[PDB]
Image (cartoon, coloured by chain):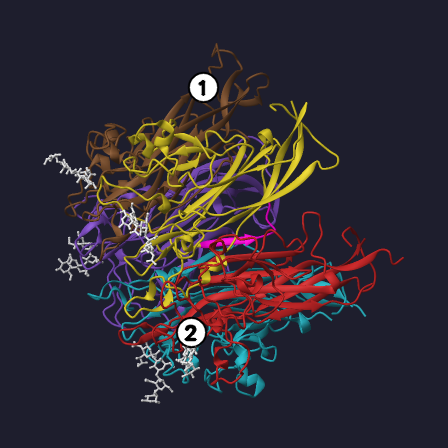
Chain colours: A yellow, B red, C cyan, D purple, E brown
């Protein structure tokens, strides 16, 4: 699989596959009930704050995590491998943020009037396509943060030891692979630029508290995945890995300004071709 | 035909058609009377808010919906090889942003201490989408709140399609919740989004900018052409000579002097589409 | 001028002309006196507000209007010649003047009446057009009930001889005009008509809000090509060249009841034209 | 130098020259003393306001003016002229705006705490390179403004008459040339688009009062000065004119919100070549 | 070293080297203890303000400084007297600021957004941002320029204009004073509010910078592994590594966090990754 040779031609030598990845903002897909917690699906549960400089214990369901899927491609086997050539990707549903008729904190709080404040604030959009899991590099705001041990994969899960001060900057010890959906918090785990030779990733961040969310969408834009040498990600064991996170901001409730993260689903249409290798 | 062959040449092989789609912000075109509701045409009616976490029922006339039109093209159709109209390009323009420079009206004023200043111009969340295709725009439903009590008359919602109430998956991507944009002023834009899993025969282009007092921004020129050809050089092909135009152009809200009532503002969109005849098999 | 043929060659087959159009924000150029109203030239007079939901009567001098000029080109004439507008270099001049924050506007510290004189801010509108005939206009208003003056401005009612209808708040094809007079057509009413203007190129942008920072760029190195997809620029009917524009920078605000005055800036045009054979 | 002919080849036919222009925000370079006014060098003195609608008398040291320099090129004389082909220009010192530890108006005025508010507000960046002085067109906010007669060059300096109402728009009578450093106020004098055939200028303006200042800087960007015919500015009598202004905004003091303009220096590196002319 | 000739071909004629530079916002990497000050690593200590117009004495640990590293490349010339030599040439760099996602932590103990009830969210990092990186074949040349020539910077612990000149700053140091120059030859020592890339030098370095000001400005960052910055000049020549030394320099300030105690601000910085492609170049 090391030496990359000619493209393979002939029947079924090119394929397209599509997938959507639902966001993982904190509330899991179940319970489905719209009274017992399912009404928060697509959102986090209410963000809970530290009680002191030394007591920061966020709930698992308040922490957005990476979405990921591993897709199995047609069996193939000088061997052949599937090569990801390009991707059309789209974040769906920004129009739903035009709902300003709900029960959020209103724009006129004196009289409880105006409109229901739309989703605003910090936004984070990353997607990746690769032929193996996305390589992750840990880096946190606060190495003292007391993440739960169960239900979430954090730096301590990997090292078996408490975070160190270097984890607030770049600590090469704190690395992982995005091998599970809805488990790796995005406030901890970042694409690792020192690895990911077989993955392309693309991200942006906009911060603030009331920042207007911005999003574009079209079915006419293709992201090429080929590297400088004309070679796309090569799918080891015919596995294709898709990873993303799409945070639009928070809604704010009428009770103590409780914030809920809002995420939106991402569509992928990947074009792949067979490549000779040895 | 599924197989796309050569361009047709000769007399009348290329045509240009134009249309404007008026916005559908909530108030219908009629009554025309400027005292009986017609004064809100181009706008929504006053946005009504939920009364609790479990009671959110927006008025239909408070919900912007998609604009659409189906235009009939000239009839077409050895008779073993057929012809279809192919949409090559579109010049499209949102008209009327200058009208937002009216700051002399009776909106909430900028100085509420003296009730002075200027009439606050339209501001806030903005949403601009257009599409051109050879069949209706494919729609994917996704809502803020699956508990929202959308009206069961006068509007097409997820429940219209499924015959069942919305579920938690409708707040993310639920592949069951799909529709086609086959009616003007009927599909709310807060529910129905272009479906990237379909629309093989339509090109769509959209953007969203949120917030409450965000300055609206717009550009307009008659010098810009959008090419509609795909990677293979093939534009949307008009099934049964029908051309579908879809759009929505929300500029923000105006706010009244009475308990900050908000009204959505929309603007009309112009389309000039160039089509050519294409041989198909 | 139906069929467009070869370019004309030879002596004086290419020409260049320049003009500036001063803004039309509401105060006319006269009286010139700086105590009798001339001090507002380049600005509107104080924006006056509706007194009810059914009583909106703006003063003519509070409404920015389109600037326009028709320039006469050198006389030319089966096969005739027309002047063809090839490109334009255009610039909005004087943004540096907005750096005057030492005047008597509403100050930045209203608590103590201190700080600086608040600079021009808010809603901005920049459009220019170059064509071989008047700019085609499409009417569209915020409020079809607005009571524009009958004299002194050209409005929808001027054209139709009838009151505005609700369709005038969206696209009503009946409500059309031509930009044939300077300082007469309000920009909150009259927009470039995308369904016409085959022989004019226009370019516009809008940024709204109340305190939005104005933005402007300027350079003498930027050329706007006016040729269409077929390589044909606007053709000047009867050797007339039409220039149209509006350049609103925002408002200044006074210390008296937050009265707003629109601010506009002049626009420079330098048009390159060439002779074109036509049949 | 009427007709422009071929490029001159051979030894020393191409030259590079560099210069920095310090900003002229209102306080002159002297006195140097940091207690006698020198502490304001790089800044204006405190902006003074009109006392009524008819009494606007700005101090000279509150008005930013154009920076300019005339550089002498190697002597040359079918004659030859120096042709400016390109310029690399940069505004230096934006990092200094990261000083938020001084005694400006603080971010928390309720308690007088936080940080020293950094420079913010209206920004103005223009540079020009030409073979003769930059041509200026006058245009003011207020034709009634009572500028000082001595110490600044204003419209009245040129016309010998008071400003007229047309000076608030485009009045072709009100023209000048940028022939002195630190003398022509930028709120009065603008690049004249009806002239400047032998100069290239590039400008932008961003307004507001608390607007975040933005600046990019790199040594990898070249501005080509050649016109549509491949001809750059031709230096009359071997003189090269550099003109600029780089306003970053204002700092605000803790005393009645007094504002001081902040300017930054601009670097220029001009490439010139010999040109045959007739 | 001066005259640039053909590219060298053959085995190991092209190489790639990578490095990360951690931010230098004010708190040093040690002590490591999360109770003794290590909890501030990645941040400045609390910004302290002037007490009058003539008394501005910032603490060293409140001043972000330039990050830098010198990488030693494989030696090329056994004999420097040969009429033709080889040098490493930096062709391009992939660079990335890592960890912006960590700013999505709004669950800590910063000043909260609901100050009436002490609720809402922990206010995220906001405000003034500064991103510069450089790659060159010798130290980055620095030009001094300060807000206030009266600022009483410590004499020990930071390299300032006075460190270089041995004299107090002059009023000209508030604009361009060509006397006030230095080289970025040490990590975590040169304050970024004092020292700027010198556009009059740096012939053998490429630098790229941007500044965004304000106090509550939303921070913005992009990251991808698909973006290459080309380092070749107008003649097709990249930085040439003098004595095989490659210099990397950067600063990446994201803004401040604000505490619940007197709105004390702490600068936040993020690390920067570099992957530099270099090739051997014949020179004489
Ligand atoms: C219901 C509750 O209080 N849950 C606590 C939880 O308390 C458990 C148990 O449920 C409770 O009966 C018992 O008295 O105490 C035990 C143990 O303490 O304790 C956990 C910590 O272990 C949490 O503190 C939890 O509180 C929830 O925490 C979530 C974050 O993990 C989140 O903040 C919840 O906030 C929301 C929510 O997302 O559910 C915010 C939301 O806006 C609210 N919705 C509305 C319409 O107001 C809801 C709502 O108040 C509650 O869900 C109850 O209907 O809370 C927070 O409750
Ligand atoms: C007129 C009214 O009260 N309408 C109610 C409606 O009341 C019905 C019935 O129509 C009415 O004649 C009767 O008195 O009572 C019954 C039942 O109570 O009930 C419906 C059902 O939900 C609505 O509540 C309706 O209220 C209107 O709802 C609209 C949204 O669907 C919108 O919010 C209307 O608000 C506006 C408007 O857009 O018309 C907002 C606008 O800014 C206002 N304009 C001005 C100049 O003030 C108008 C204005 O108050 C009224 O239209 C004048 O009657 O209302 C809202 O009225
Ligand atoms: C002076 C006045 O109030 N004028 C009215 C006008 O009244 C006329 C006549 O002029 C007056 O002497 C008489 O008492 O009444 C008659 C008829 O009623 O009536 C018209 C309507 O037909 C207007 O209401 C007009 O008021 C002016 O309207 C302008 C817009 O059309 C504008 O708002 C004027 O406001 C300014 C101005 O732009 O001139 C705002 C400006 O900021 C002010 N300048 C300063 C330094 O304060 C001036 C200034 O107050 C006045 O011009 C007095 O010198 O007013 C508005 O006055
Ligand atoms: C010192 C003073 O009052 N200067 C006046 C000047 O007064 C002269 C003379 O100096 C004075 O002793 C005498 O009593 O009166 C005469 C003439 O009346 O008069 C001129 C007009 O001719 C000015 O009004 C001047 O005031 C200064 O004007 C500057 C603008 O030209 C500027 O606003 C000055 O404001 C600053 C400054 O820039 O120097 C603003 C600055 O933020 C302040 N610094 C601090 C740390 O507070 C300083 C400071 O207050 C003074 O410099 C005193 O050291 O003032 C303004 O003073
Ligand atoms: C602790 C203190 O006051 N330190 C002073 C320092 O005082 C030393 C000595 O530590 C102290 O015991 C004694 O009273 O006096 C000596 C000598 O005077 O004096 C220096 C000046 O020489 C400083 O004034 C220092 O104060 C610290 O200054 C830092 C900037 O250099 C910074 O502002 C510190 O502020 C923080 C911090 O960054 O550590 C801000 C931070 O948000 C705070 N964290 C929390 C959770 O509140 C901490 C915290 O209050 C202190 O570290 C104590 O735990 O302070 C500032 O303290």
Which residue is outermost to the right?
B78
On the rendering, which quadrant does ligand 2 occupy?
A: bottom left
Is residue E8 positioned above or below B120 on the image? above
Q: Nearer the viewer, residue D24 or C125?
A: C125
**Residue at 63% across, 70% down:** C195
Label 2's element? loop
> In the displayed structure, does residue A158 sit left or right of residue D197?
left
Q: Quadrant of residue B273?
A: bottom right
Q: Nearer the viewer's eye, disc 2 or disc 1? A: 2
Under tag 1, what secondary structure?
Answer: loop
Q: Is residue D68 above or below residue C75?
A: above
What x and y, as percent, mark residue D104? 22, 51
In this view, C259 is above or below A227: below
| Residue D8 inside the magenta-drawn segment | no
Residue bounds of the magenta highlight: A214-222
Which chain's residue wears label 1?
E
Residue matched to label 2: B46
Measuring from the top left, give residue D277's x and y in whole percent. Answer: 59, 45
Q: Position of residue E163 (x, y in %)?
A: 24, 30
**Viewer-side residue, D160 vs A113:** A113
Are labels 2 and 1 on one chain? no
Q: In the image, which disc is placed on residue E73?
A: 1
């Amino acid at each position: 699989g090391m030496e990359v040779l000619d493209l393979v031609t002939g029947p079924d030598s090119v394929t397209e596959i599509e997938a959507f990845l639902n966001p993982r903002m904190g509330q899991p897909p179940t319970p489905e009930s719209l009274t017992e917690g399912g009404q928060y699906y697509g959102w986090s549960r209410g963000i809970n704050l530290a009680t002191s400089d030394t007591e920061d214990s966020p709930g698992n369901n308040t922490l957005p995590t990476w979405s990921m899927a591993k897709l199995q491609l047609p069996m193939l086997n000088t061997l052949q491998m599937w090569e990801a050539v390009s991707v059309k990707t789209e974040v769906v549903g920004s129009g739903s943020l035009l709902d300003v008729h709900g029960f959020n904190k209103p724009t006129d709080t004196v009289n409880t009037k105006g409109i229901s404040t739309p989703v605003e604030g910090s936004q984070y959009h990353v997607f990746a396509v690769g032929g193996e899991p996305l390589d992750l590099q840990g880096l946190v705001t606060d190495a003292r943060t007391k993440y739960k041990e169960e239900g979430v994969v954090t730096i301590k899960t990997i090292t078996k030891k408490d975070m160190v001060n270097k984890d607030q900057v770049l600590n090469p010890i704190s690395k992982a692979k995005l091998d599970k959906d809805g488990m790796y918090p995005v406030e901890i785990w970042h694409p690792d630029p020192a690895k990911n030779e077989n993955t392309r990733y693309f991200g942006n961040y906009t911060g603030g508290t009331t920042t207007p969310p911005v999003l574009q969408f079209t079915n006419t834009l293709t992201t090429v995945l080929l590297d400088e040498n004309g070679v796309g990600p090569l799918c080891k064991g015919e596995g294709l890995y898709l990873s993303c996170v799409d945070i639009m901001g928070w809604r704010v409730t009428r009770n103590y300004d409780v914030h809920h993260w809002r995420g939106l689903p991402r569509y992928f249409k990947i074009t792949l071709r067979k490549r000779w290798v040895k």
